[PDB]
Length: 47
Image 1 (spheres, rainbow, N blue to C red):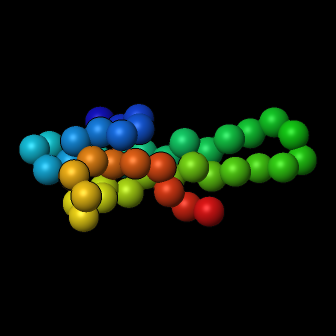
Image 2: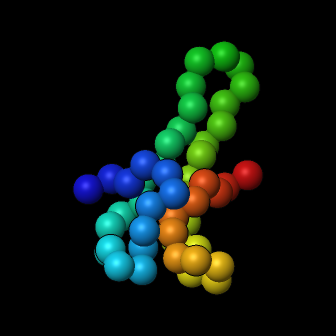
């Protein structure tokens, strides 16, 4: 169900999960949006 990183969105309708980092005072919420402007895959985002 949940996607990982750099997945096909064009020929695949799957929910792009969010990889949020932990540990340490500095946090980071790595998201994944379906980009269809270049090729058509879900790449990292949010920042």
